[PDB]
Image (cartoon, rainbow, N blue to C red; front, side):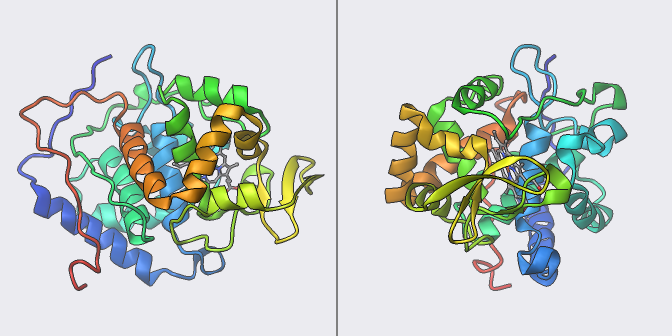
Amino acid sequence: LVHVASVEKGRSYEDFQKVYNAIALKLREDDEYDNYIGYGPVLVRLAWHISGTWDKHDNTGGSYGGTYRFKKEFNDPSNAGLQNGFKFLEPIHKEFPWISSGDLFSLGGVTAVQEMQGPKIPWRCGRVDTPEDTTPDNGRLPDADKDAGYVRTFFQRLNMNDREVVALKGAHALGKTHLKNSGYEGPWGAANNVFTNEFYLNLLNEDWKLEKNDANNEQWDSKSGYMMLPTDYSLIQDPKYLSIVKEYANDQDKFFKDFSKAFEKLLENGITFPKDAPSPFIFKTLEEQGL
Ligand code: HEM
């Protein structure tokens, strides 16, 4: 498979900035979701899950085709709870019907991070909706009950190396696990709708205790009311992941620079960009626009 990026006909930066502004104004307005965390965390999880089905060996899956819109991918057990982010973005797609699905799903992720005080993520347009038979089969997204060797091997399929994996995992400072969605319960930290290096500080500074939860799954719990998944706790069990966790705990700007590079790569995997194509767009926040 080759997937060539094709700009939506006649659209330039200013058009996409209007779709960004619409997603950001609605994030601001629907602040009450999930006990006032808001929709920013489930929108960066949606952008990672439509991207995380990619396989580097045959170029199948990934954000290009916007195939989450189809029943098979939408109803994947690993995607439980993402229907809330889909329902958020659906009025925005009625307002701007020209944008492709993959481009809307991935721009929701970008808008969420930037509006939650995260780094600027460069974004490229050009995903094209592909037919229902290109929808990847279920089971390509990662398990949480596993160790650091699983994590490394999994992320190799998306060709992410160690630095990219630890930077990307730092998005778990956002939101929380929900027992009904995944069999796990609790937040990773206290400021869970502001993007910071808090995941790494909690992982190095809390007194974590291994316990089973109400779904019979193991998780690491701390006195503070926070939790860590087995795959998260893995990052301090592996010697190579642990030196990077410490680096991000001591330097949030290095974490923001690397998270930015890796999250753009993850959203662009599987897509060929012609050099006639526009450069990646940097969108202004509502705040930079006085809106
Ligand atoms: C081995 C890797 C990963 C595993 C096993 C994993 C697993 C999980 C699980 C079990 C949840 C909770 C789902 C729920 O109950 O609602 C979750 C939530 C979340 N994940 Fe991950 N994750 C991984 C990687 C990532 C990456 C790479 C990103 C983003 C760049 C990410 C972003 C999020 C966010 C922001 C949430 C919170 C969603 C919400 O609050 O509703 N995750 N993850």
